[PDB]
Image (cartoon, grey):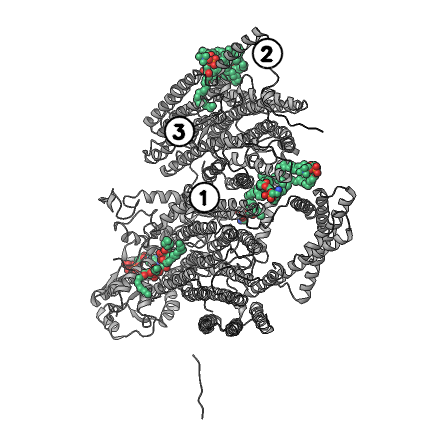
Amino acid sequence: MNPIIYTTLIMTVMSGTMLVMISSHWLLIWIGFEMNLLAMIPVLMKNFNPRATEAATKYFLTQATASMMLMMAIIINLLYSGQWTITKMFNPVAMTMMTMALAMKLGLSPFHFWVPEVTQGISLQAGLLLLTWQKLAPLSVLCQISQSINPNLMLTMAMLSILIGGWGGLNQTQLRKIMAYSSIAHMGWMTAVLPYNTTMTILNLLIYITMTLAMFMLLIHSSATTTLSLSHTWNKMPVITSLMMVTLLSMGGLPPLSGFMPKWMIIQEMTKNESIIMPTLMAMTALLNLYFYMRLAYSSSLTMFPSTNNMKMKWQFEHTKQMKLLPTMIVLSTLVLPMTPALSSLN
Amino acid sequence: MPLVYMNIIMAFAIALAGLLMYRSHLMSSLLCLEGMMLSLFIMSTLIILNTHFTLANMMPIILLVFAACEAALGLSLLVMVSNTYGTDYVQNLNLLQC
Amino acid sequence: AKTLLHKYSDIPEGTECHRKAYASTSIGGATGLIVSAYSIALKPPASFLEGVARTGRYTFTSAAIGAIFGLTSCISAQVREKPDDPLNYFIGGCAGGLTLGARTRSYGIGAAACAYMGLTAALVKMGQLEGWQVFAEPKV
Amino acid sequence: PPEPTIRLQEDPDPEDENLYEKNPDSHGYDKDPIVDLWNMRVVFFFGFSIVLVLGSTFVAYLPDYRMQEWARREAERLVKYREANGLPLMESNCFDPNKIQLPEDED
Amino acid sequence: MLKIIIPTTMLLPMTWMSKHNMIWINATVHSLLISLISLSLLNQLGENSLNFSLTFFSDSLSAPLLVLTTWLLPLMLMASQSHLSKETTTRKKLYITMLILLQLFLIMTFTATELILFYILFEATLVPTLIIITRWGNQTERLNAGLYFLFYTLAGSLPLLVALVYIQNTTGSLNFLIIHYWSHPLSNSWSNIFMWLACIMAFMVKMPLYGLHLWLPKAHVEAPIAGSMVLAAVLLKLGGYGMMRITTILNPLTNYMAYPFLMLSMWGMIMTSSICLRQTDLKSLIAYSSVSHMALVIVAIMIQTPWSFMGATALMIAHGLTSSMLFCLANTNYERVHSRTMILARGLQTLLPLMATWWLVASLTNLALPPSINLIGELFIITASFSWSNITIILMGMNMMITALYSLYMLITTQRGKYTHHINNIKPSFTRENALMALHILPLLLLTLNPKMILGPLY
Amino acid sequence: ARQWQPDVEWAEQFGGAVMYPTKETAHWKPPPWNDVDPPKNLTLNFGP
Amino acid sequence: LQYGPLAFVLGERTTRKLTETSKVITVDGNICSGKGRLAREIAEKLGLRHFPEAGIHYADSTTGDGKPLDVQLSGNCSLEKFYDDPKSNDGNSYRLQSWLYASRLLQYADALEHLLSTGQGVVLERSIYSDFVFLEAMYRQGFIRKQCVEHYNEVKKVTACEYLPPHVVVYVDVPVPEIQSRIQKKGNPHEMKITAAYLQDIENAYKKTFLPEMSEKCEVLQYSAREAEDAEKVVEDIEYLKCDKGPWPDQDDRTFHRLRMLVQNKLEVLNYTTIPVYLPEITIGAHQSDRVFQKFTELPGRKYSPGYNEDVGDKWIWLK
Amino acid sequence: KSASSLLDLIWLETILPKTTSFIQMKMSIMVSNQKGLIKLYFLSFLITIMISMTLFN
Ligand SMILES: CCCCCCCCCCCCCCCCC[C@@H](O)O[C@H](CO[C@H](O)CCCCCCCCCCCCCCC)COP(=O)(O)OCC[N+](C)(C)C
Ligand SMILES: CCCCCCCCCCCCCCCCC[C@@H](O)O[C@H](CO[C@H](O)CCCCCCCCCCCCCCC)COP(=O)(O)OCC[N+](C)(C)C
Ligand SMILES: CCCCCCCC/C=C\CCCCCCCC(=O)O[C@H](COC(=O)CCCCCCC/C=C/CCCCCCCC)COP(=O)(O)OCCN
Ligand SMILES: Nc1ncnc2c1ncn2[C@@H]1O[C@H](COP(=O)(O)OP(=O)(O)O)[C@@H](O)[C@H]1O
């Protein structure tokens, strides 16, 4: 599309998220969600093909249903208390419907079904934006009303999200579906600490955002969307495959990498409130995410797959467009474990 | 909590269930969304008028406006989907599978 | 809801075997119906009759498993004269696993179910004794 | 079946190269004779001459920080004292009972 | 402690800035110098410890392991020099970088005044080992091996982390000194039973225990020679160090809980020693021998007596050196024959006499011939277990007999008899290999002169 | 003499639509290399 | 200021550069026909830029220095081997065909980039369109298998679905006995071995498929040997006709911007020429791939980016 | 026969690693096998909403 139009749409998405974040009125939060949804669709349909249109319409359906449920919860909360301010929810299942609407917006289980579909349909840049920036507003709203959640429902949905992401990532060959299931699992990890510490939720969100940005921008640099297509990258850019494998190891939660920091902290926080069984189950389930990350690493850098004759020509050319923030993203997603106590900055 | 509010919430729940059944005709999904919107408008209007929240009289109109815009967007999407297949059948969108 | 949990937990472990069996059967039927609903929603097998047959099969299997587990767990606890012992729950769980295997007609699955259920039931009894919280309320 | 019976374009598996044919006195370190000889020399000098001998001499003559001779002399002076006064060598109680306050049972 | 850590870190820029044909020389020289520096830690005291700072402390349990870890790197470089000849300079530098990172992680792990830092480095050792196994392994099974070597470990270690943080929520600290000085008895409760299991199984999977030993033959057979050496010599001892450090808070629950693991180890040493008798693979045989020896070390740690701890320390050091030497010998055979099967290359004493002498010495020291430190550890553990129960002596005697049997079987099958006729590519042994075996074996016979240097903090 | 590296047969395991093909998912086909699928004016007669 | 969204936003619009003489033309003909002469004369008379027919080392002429690289580092195939042993065991024929198609794709991208950036028209020999005819002939003569043509069709679809076809297609029609005579007179020993059936198959694939398919979206000027001699008549025919049936008239500023961003960044142009479909003729194993890539890296000015090669003579490296 | 093949190569392998692989593979096949029909997903969402409304209060 026109670069001016694309810039305007991106700024409108950001402005909707910011309106959700800075407002104290429920109607304004709903308006910000509506603005973000309105400006998001053409970004998902930049490259015109039937798959992109299908993904966009699925995303629109899910987000519109979530917005209607959110407004319904707001209306019930207003009925049982003449309050518009975003505070304690003041009521039963009105809060349940608010939690369900925010879970559908975030993609938490059992409302996770749209994430792999939309991520596979859209391109890599649209997937990057969808899996990174579209989590800030619902997570902020959840953090604001985190004193109101029913811990049983939130913890059940978080555990279901972790289990579903771990199990669904095992069966995937397409990279975008792998990213979607990884996002589902990481959201499950994020929302299981909301009742206890929102600071840990924000730290996990920051780490996941950095790691996902590095992952998606590496995938964009080596333009592959499939496991076998990614298996050809070693014959042109071995350093990209090595950085990709290190990033994948970080995403698996392996110490001393950065991806270990959130889970660790979360587990610690969870043991401060006499919760022992659920952190253990969460770690045993994250082992599955680690397994399919390790399989991708095997196919990517640790082994040399067969190539094609035409690749020789690609040896004579260089990438014209370069991402400036990729080295910083890789370093941040890999080597900031020693700086853990800085989480006191209430990130 | 009176009975008219219960009836309106029951209408909202029925519209949501109809949206979630998905027999065919994505247009029916859009219709269910608009029915849920109408229920929300009616009940918010009743709550605001009953308690004489004078300023909150802005809220219904706004809602309406925004939601109607959503409908337009949805309609547009439907057209493009039809422009690929000629019909708005739900089962035609099976190219993506989890 | 928690009504079935209260009904099962209120009865003493070593007394009223039939009441415990009934509560366990009710819980098993509920979870079987829920699983059948999930399966039907995700996968419509062929038709209404096949769907209701699958629902009945799943529900009666789960109800039988719950019944067998409850009777064995209660009978073992009563005869051994040592209430609040996870070993009885293990045996009850083991018996339940065996009946599932007999239903599905596989020695391996039956054997596998017996070992796993025995472990899960013992863990649940241990958590009841020690007050382990699966869903911990926010403390600090 | 017009297939070439070749799955792909593969280099033939090379034969192992012997360091003794191109260089007798090969030491098994490198193909370059100078780098080979100097690798052998540095390995031998820093492994056998420096670490194995000087480190062994250093460990052998480590000062008595475990206090073995100190403990022996302490024991000799203590037993000399106790034999002289007739005290019954080592006591059964490590800590004197008068400084311990037992809890009275009164059962 | 930084006087050892900083040079190890500086090994990386020096390796990456070295000339294309001077990486091995520089790495070997500076690793040997770092080992000479690390020798200073052996001057311990009968008092508490060598507490350098709030982060790192030394002990006469930590010091021998640190010295062995530093000494192993030059040998690993010398053995890897052979099969990496046809490799690009960047990949050789990456291999050396992996080795240096492994050494740094082990050095920081063995001091580790705090338990969470110990856990972080104890798992940090995983990544370089996994990369080395799955990148520079020869066969197609290496990938599978790597998976095993990873997941087993994590299956034991993720619960431990939970337990660790739980302890810090109750005790208030995880410092080793505060943990020892403020230790309180563990009540016999189900919660305490599962805390014991979580604290223990992470280290018991790394020894490994007899029931959990499946990953070890795969990882040892599939890894390159340096990977095999670092796995058999140091990485197996991390579990023993962890159990020795963590059993302080587990008393008196250890008395009841130790029975299943004692039975598993006492029967598994016999089982694995018998397995060694029928083996068509040299590396698999050496791996199963390692399993048997670490089963004995597990028995020693579980019995929890001063003689048990001294014998266990001595046996870990001795087994590390001996197993590394055995793997090196098998690798020297493989680099000539390219098969790694015991029965194919025969009668090698006639063709390589000095290598046969090295084989004989390695087999003798694996067979626990007195007064070698192998025998010292074996005998101390046996005496402590006899004091524990007089019926253990039957199992230990059986293990000794089978150990002698399979050690001499491995020696006779490869060195004695008639040479294979068609195998004609057996060149004379290089100076590098003979120097490698000499540098493996001389420290053992020097340490038998001063056993108290490797007898641990309970000496 | 040489380190083993994956061949065509090994690589073809990862070329399916999903991992672990089943009887139900055997008929699934990988998506196109570019995310584009084949797409697969009226007349009026004004008479008297 | 390298071209991108910023340049388009500020001033850079390519519609104002079009001055009704761009008119990309491709000249097609059989083997040993005088299509190159006609293309050169057309380019000279109409003031356009001529593109010589893409060969094995066309890509080498555009990167680094223009000198061609080694055959094993660039193409891994030879036309002389195809002429000698068209049924060779190592699958050289389809490797040659695929490399030549990819070279034509790169050349078409370069020509489109020049047309869109300068406005000056271009003249081309056989393009990505009509490249299939050789493939077709190679299939009927038994030189290549059906899997080869299936892979070619997949790659051709995915690649060529992104470009605008040429404005005018010029065809030079010559009978088979005549170019057999011309081939004999040429003097190339490898060209003497071309059979009459192969040339007949090429000519049949041209007329049966290429001209009818280009007729509904391009304008075709069928010419014989005699009336292709005079380029004045050809140029007069080019100038008289006006193109209003192809996809060019409906293009606008944003479509041109997308096409210009696509034709730049040749790595994305060649993206689908290496799809992970394993045909024994073209697939290369890990060990040979590693060795050949390492050899390519050891080339003088190829280890680093074009401006960061000290051995070639680049200075001020530490401040770039 | 017993120590090497029966226990080490078969049963110790059957218990921990092989059973885990089998269970995880079966669960992955079950979870990931969705035909992409929003009808089934929406019905499941409705069932979940009803279950949560009837269970968590
Ligand atoms: C080839 C055939 C033989 C030819 C040579 C003939 C000569 C033979 C003599 C050699 C052996 C025969 C035995 C003679 C023994 C004399 C030496 C012995 O008495 O000294 C020992 C000393 O040896 C050392 O204690 C042991 C060596 C140190 C071991 C460290 C290894 C070196 C570091 C390299 C890296 C380590 C890798 C392994 C990690 C742990 C014991 O000393 P100690 O009774 O106490 O007190 C010494 C004096 N004090 C009282 C002042 C302190
Ligand atoms: C796979 C290769 C080996 C892997 C590692 C194996 C080692 C782990 C084995 C764990 C050791 C035993 C666990 C618990 C030991 C407690 C002692 C108990 O067994 O004895 C009786 C306990 O009675 C019964 O055993 C009760 C438990 C029965 C249920 C446990 C399952 C039994 C077999 C399961 C083994 C499967 C292990 C692997 C799981 C995947 C004593 O009766 P009681 O006085 O009342 O209890 C005393 C403890 N109190 C005081 C805290 C209450
Ligand atoms: C090599 C692979 C083997 C895998 C290792 C398995 C052994 C580890 C044990 C299983 C996990 C338990 C982790 C416990 C973490 C320590 C924390 C703790 O002990 O605190 C207890 C917590 O105890 C528990 O909650 C235990 C519940 C266990 C739930 C998960 C069970 C996992 C499967 C267990 C069956 C296997 C048992 C033997 C395994 C041996 C290895 C094969 C007290 O809880 P609170 O409520 O805070 O105390 C107040 C009331 N007194
Ligand atoms: N697609 C192709 N496949 C195989 N060979 C080709 C292909 N395209 C061109 N060639 C070869 O390029 C050579 C030059 O073509 P031609 O037009 O006959 O000569 P000239 O350049 O003198 O006009 C010819 O020998 C022809 O075979």
- Give the camera-side residue of D75 and D104: D104
Instruction: Name the residue nearer the viewer: E195 or A321.
Output: E195
Q: Quadrant of the N terminus of chain E?
A: top left
Position of residue F1 measured from the top left corner of the image (x, y, whole percent): 45, 35
Residue at disc 3, secondary structure: helix
Q: Amino acid at mark 2?
A: Leu
- Chain letter of the residue beneath label 1 in the structure image: A
Nearest to the observer: residue E11 or residue B42: B42
Asked whether, in this view, residue E14 is left or right of residue E251, the answer is left
Q: Nearer the viewer, mark 1 or mark 2?
A: 2
Q: Residue G226: percent from the left, percent from the top?
A: 26, 69
Q: Which label number is shown at residue D89?
A: 2
Outermost residue, bottom side? F48
User: Is G240 left, or right, of E180 in this rendering?
Assistant: left
Picture coordinates of residue G97 (x, y %)?
Answer: 38, 56
Instruction: Identify residue for label 3.
Output: E4
**Which chain's residue wears label 3?**
E
Q: Chain of mark 2?
A: D
- Lateral position of residue D104 relative to residue E344, left or right: right
Label 1, label 2: how many angstroms apart (C-alpha)?
A: 72 Å
Going by the numbered disc 1, the residue's amino acid type is Thr
Image spot of residue E115 (x, y percent)? 50, 35
Residue A344 to residue G122: above or below: above
Q: Which residue is mark 1?
A: A303
Query: Would you say the residues marked 1 and 3 are in contact, meaning their CB atoms lie under 8 Å apart?
Result: no
Query: Residue E100 is drawn in which quadrant?
Result: top left
- Mark 2 sits near ligand 1, with its Cβ under 8 Å away: no
Do badges 1 and 2 share one subunit? Answer: no
